[PDB]
Length: 294
Length: 293
Ligand SMILES: O=C(Nc1nccs1)[C@@H](c1cc(F)ccc1O)N1Cc2ccc(-c3ccc(N4CCNCC4)cc3)cc2C1=O
Ligand SMILES: O=C(Nc1nccs1)[C@@H](c1cc(F)ccc1O)N1Cc2ccc(-c3ccc(N4CCNCC4)cc3)cc2C1=O
Ligand SMILES: Nc1ncnc2c1ncn2[C@@H]1O[C@H](COP(=O)(O)OP(=O)(O)NP(=O)(O)O)[C@@H](O)[C@H]1O
Ligand SMILES: *CCC(=O)N[C@@H]1CN(c2nc(Nc3cn(C)nc3OC)c3ncn(C)c3n2)C[C@H]1F
Ligand SMILES: [Mg+2]
Image (cartoon, rainbow over all chains, first blue to last red; front, side):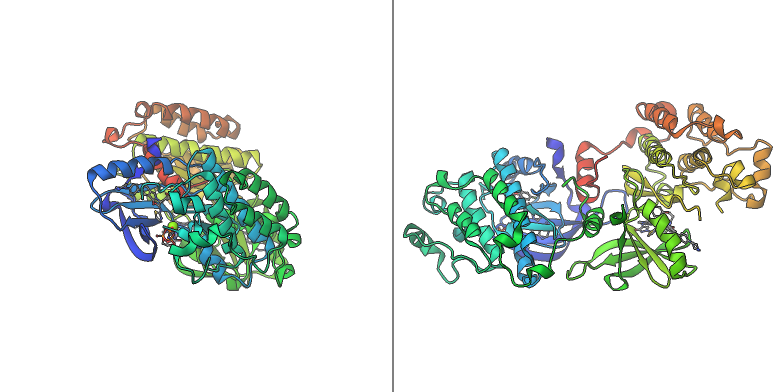
């Protein structure tokens, strides 16, 4: 339990390059230098923007231990932490980056089999979090990391103590209610991001006005590639009654069914000239970059 | 089977830095660039020196398919091959490098628990090769790679198609390579570790090694070894190959000693060096070593 989170010294790692920032901190590509060794191991470091105290660090560590305890192929695990004035968190470096930027950059080369399997994998990761009784609270295409093109993992979950209005359920925007069913709403928006190849939700609508349009029944529009089958699932994630939305267990089953006949459910120009990697290319990826069980 | 070896194009990988030289080639640090992608993935690439032909490239492929088929935590797997003028072989990059240089560079910080566990892991990999009926033929501290300090893996095995001072007497005299002649090389490999990377028979010409072996000379007892460990090494160097221990037996014996390491190795400073905590091991595995055992 306690051994799943490594406490690092300042002197055993170095930030080398800025990767981006968001709302809670700046993420760096970094290097871990094991004591007494000559190797340099790449890591990802998030330095929280707000400085904290030793007593606030007790809060940080209590949540850090929980996020260091996850064990699922599609959920990222927090690996380490270094406390000072500013808190630095350490996890595995994902060279492919986040799924949002990945789909924007590869939008003319992503076929139906990839998109639906990513939907399955995110639902598998979310179902694990629900099983562990951990609410994500910030699910979005930007918080799905690409380990390999065939394998995505959820990150930045459970930040209860630390707003993405356009990804939040109506009950979260108004009354600050965060449940696994409000995550299902965020899952719907994330799927919309993938199927629009990285479009911005409610583009040009100020965040302060999102709750009004949701109450009047407006929802994100049907993406051009989505059949009605897929759009019905997205819409059901955005029902105003949280208990009427699908469960992550059901989303796994439904998207897995569609993944077994992907061109029936997504209409993409060029779909027959793109496929999943052959077993050869998957074995090569996994041996070099992805040796975990699944 | 066939899908375990990836055939790469010249245009999808690049050699960036020379790491050293091995069997039949120079091993380089490389980068794999997946087609249609922007990432660069580090690999280790060996470009065969004596260049080859398309008909000869078939012999290479038949052996490559077997070395791409190994599935054991302590045995390195061949991942890819690029059939160019010179044939280049692709596998996972081990930033820690080989165990021989590692023990030389960390010789004042390596405790008994690491040394005995390294012996266990090499024996596990060699027992695997025996189970697959693959004779290594070149086992040595140089052909044991460090994935993490806690996890070593055997490489460059099965190159049937000379390391005299690691060879069993029957290999030197008669070119007989069996799993029992590997046991001899394993004994020498353990000797390299326990001496913190000393050269075996230092200063004796290779052309005279078989003579000294026939007269009964063997590598001397390393200073840190108790007699229990040295007796095992000596039993690996018996002239009767069938009298040498089996890798299955070496696993059991070294694992027993690994459960009480300071009883079997006497190292100055041993009580101030230990294995990594579960904390440090989980950190290593998540970053560098996500494979099972
Ligand atoms: O480190 C993460 N990302 C990374 N990106 C790149 C490199 S590291 C993710 C993260 C990474 C994962 F891999 C998996 C889950 C996860 O959540 N974390 C972890 C984390 C732990 C604790 C806290 C925390 C708790 C309390 C407080 N307050 C309370 C009120 N005022 C005083 C102090 C502030 C911050 C935040 C986070 C966080 O953002
Ligand atoms: O690639 C390896 N090392 C690496 N270092 C760094 C990056 S890759 C290991 C290696 C890697 C493993 F993962 C496991 C075992 C192993 O041996 N190989 C593999 C290999 C395959 C084939 C051949 C081969 C066979 C026959 C011929 N003849 C045929 C008849 N006409 C004349 C020429 C030439 C070359 C050699 C090797 C070899 O040296
Ligand atoms: N382990 C990682 N490896 C590589 N890039 C990462 C990693 N973790 C996060 N990033 C990226 O680093 C950038 C900045 O991180 P972050 O501060 O979380 O921004 P963000 O995720 O887009 N905003 P947020 O909604 O709070 O998660 C984003 O592009 C992340 O996708
Ligand atoms: C110890 C004997 C030796 O040097 N053999 C050479 C190098 N080998 C080798 N090395 C690595 N990793 C490595 C070595 N150095 C100096 N830096 C690195 O990593 C950046 C390696 N990874 C995978 N393979 C197959 C390797 N081989 C073997 C001989 F080339
Ligand atoms: Mg994030």
